[PDB]
Every structure is written in structure tokens, then in C-alpha cells.
Length: 285
Length: 285
Image (cartoon, rainbow over all chains, first blue to last red; front, side, top):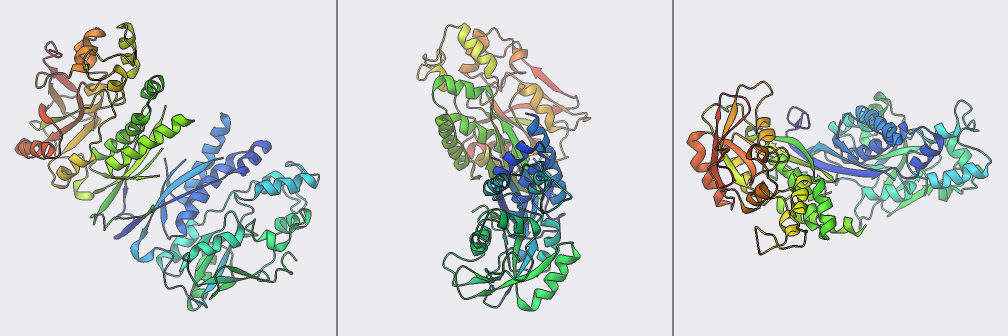
């Protein structure tokens, strides 16, 4: 009831970390569509995903009948993340063992980047998406031209994935060296945050390592969005980027899939600041 | 920057506790008066004072140009409590050693109640106070008839005291067995919360052990408020009630005064559920 026994939770050297994030335009999409339960899940997912990149298990979370529908989603999001419930914004508190806190300072050139699939746009890029959908003469309750089994609104309102459960096992085992929750600004803006402001290291991202999900292929064509713009606006099907040493890449991938997260090798660390893209001319085929 | 090293903070067996409280009508008083910096301090004081009763040091706190003035008060309140900043409502997170968490289960009949003076009404009872002031033909910017050196508004807007600093030393030394932050409902509603719902123990409060502060003597007369009503509505000059064993009463009092809190013996624990008052006919003289 508000108090958490950290030792009973398994922590003998706990470090407290705090995360915060918001939703934004996706709420306007939930309004115009009528269903708001997902945006409550998004507010939790975004907040707790910002904790897991540091290796922390979430503990607390804090943030009209519209408000009633969202609060039910927040509840569903906490149950999926495993934390206690206390333009939108959320705040979560988590804990991580001192020896397991991320990112580590052992990151070097040659380390491998892994990618976790996203459920969709998550909670970023909806201002542009709405424009592309409208100019294509579509409405939220139309059948999605890329997924005939669902409507445009439902596909866009798909809740942000919660990456707490599938990552904690590898965090406890020291399989990961750093992570980046892919939110606004795509790969270009998010991945560099793993390194220091004056770090000589960056990443090389192989955009041919996977096939673009259908929703992004459609948005890319319907909106005449060039590949270099896609990777700077949307998550492009990747919800989380994780850096791991080469000798641990197999174990990390096995752990992620064991916990139900589709993962693959998407790039590598190199001695060049920023994000460098391979196959920009093939991205989207 | 959002992360707290609990071991570095001195905790080898930390327990996390969460506190929450609001201000309420005192904000309307700040509006009608023009100065809102104090209500920001109140929102912090109330939240952190609900943590200290459990023995916990506050760590995090979270909650128009009116909003600008209050945020400055919240800042001033966090600096006084020592926590990091993240009808109003606040939420604070604190930490306490397992062996120091309060209340203890060793409370028994014969233990002594100590009282800490309040700065004024703190954050409760302003609906009735406003009525009494108005019917007395006074306004917020009139000179307080009980304190000629200040105005009615300033005296009523006095910020709630922060009891973190003067209590932590005694919490670490195990001098206290339990506390009750006196908020709404006066002694009658707050003190019983220290015990279990089915506890056979209560308290005997000696209302002749101290002189009522001038503001309460005035409100008691101006508003024709009977003593049994005072102790069920206002804090009556006592911001915190603390239970201590008889053999530790001297040490506790010495510790509280050493840290600048005027404290005195106000009652004792006895085998009778509820709050029992002594000297109700003398209260206010």
C-alpha cells in the first residue's frame, strides 16, 4: 500500500531512477475516433520504457468521461508493466541494482545494435500521419488499406509496447550495455542519446536488415516521404535499440525472443559521431 | 539528475514510502489576497510531513501567472524539506531504514504524547475561518486583531511548517514510536490513525498543558466556537503529535528543541479507543 520493500524485491544495492514522458497528438486521434483506452496504456508504456533503458524496474506511476476511459488504460498499462498506480504527461519511479545500471561505460566500436519491433507509431508522429491519411481520402473508421482486418483508427491507436518484462531478464544477466527508447525524431535523434555529448562513438544502421512493416510502407508512399525523412520522424517499426558486445549478441537475441520480443541485428557501433544509414535507397521495399 | 544513490544516502536496508496530500481552500485565500508563494510551500510541507510520520526522508516531489507564483513556493518548500522537485494535490516519495520505520508495534498504555507547535492554520479549516473573519467585519488586508504586526491575510497564509529536519535525527536514534500529522479534523480525527483499526489503545490529551496561540483564542471567541468543536476542526497550535516511551521523553524533547522545534508533553497513551480530552472547559484561556 504505497510502501515497497526493496530487499524483498531482490535489491541489495538499489539505485532509484525517475522517468517521464507524454503522449501528445495521439490523444486527439483517440478523441476523433471515440476510443481512448489505448492512450492510457501509451502514457504508462512511454514512462516505463524510459526507465528500462537505464535497467530499472518500474515501481510507481503517476499522471469528463474521456478521463474515465483513459484511467482504465493507465490501469491496464501498469498491470502490463508491473508497477503500482498512484497533451498528457506521466511520471514513473523505478529501481536498478548498482551493478546492473545502464548504459555501461564499456561501449566501444564493434559492438552490435539489436532492434525490437514496435507495435506501430506508438505515441509519436501523429501530426504528419493525420495529414497523410486525410489527403489520401481516408477517415479513421475506414478499413486500413495496409491491413484489411482493421480500421485506420485502430491501427493508429495501437498502444505503445511495454518492454519491461522481456528486458529485465537480460538486464539482470548483464547481457546489455545500453538502450534507446525510440520516440520522437526516429533513429537520428534517439540513438545518439546512449553516448556522451562529446563521445567519439556513433552507430551504423543497416536499413536492409529487415522489411518495413506495411503501415510504414503505406505511409511512406501515400505521404511521399523520403527515406531520410522517415528515419528522422517515425520509429519505422523499431521500438527499442539495444547495444550489446559481439560475444553476447547470440545470448541477448535468444533472451529477447524467449520473452516474446522479435529481435534482430540492425547495426553496429563505430568511431563516428551520429547515426549513419546504410541502404537508404532500398528502405521501404 | 533524477537518480538517487540510496547507499550513498546512508541506507543499507531502504524501504520506500509514498505520501500524498492537498491544500484546498487556502488557495482561494491566496487568490483573494494576491500572494500565492505560501500555498506552494504548503503543498510540499503537507506531502513531506505525511512521509516523516513513517520515519522517511523525502526524495522526490511532484504536483496563469498564479501558477508561476506557486511553483516558486514549491521550490522553496523542496529546499526546506531537502527533496528534488519533479484545489491542489501533491505527491512525494521518501525512504526509511527498515529498522527505523514508524509507527512501531511496541506502543502501549503509559507512553507519552509530545506536541510540536504549528505555524498557524497550516492548510486546513479555511472555509470556517473565512466565515468568522467576514462576520467580524474584517478583510484580508486589515491588521490582524490578534497580531498587530501583520495583516489577517498574511497570518492566515502562513505556510505549513516542514517537520523533516527536526525529526530525522530522532528517527535515526529510535527516540520515537509513532507520529500523526495534524491536518483536517483536528486531534480527534488524526491521532487515532497511529493505531490499528481494532486497537484497544487511544490517548488522553491535556488541553491545559499549553496556552492557546492568539490566533486560535481570537477565532474561538469571534466565531463562538466551543472547545469540543475546536479540537475537531483546527490544529489548535499543534502541527504534529508524537508518541514516545516514558523513559525516552526527556531525550526526545531535548532532540526536538535542539533542532529548533518547540515541544512539550501534551498527553499519554491509555487503554481506551479514541481521543479523550482533559480541561475542555479551560481550553482557550
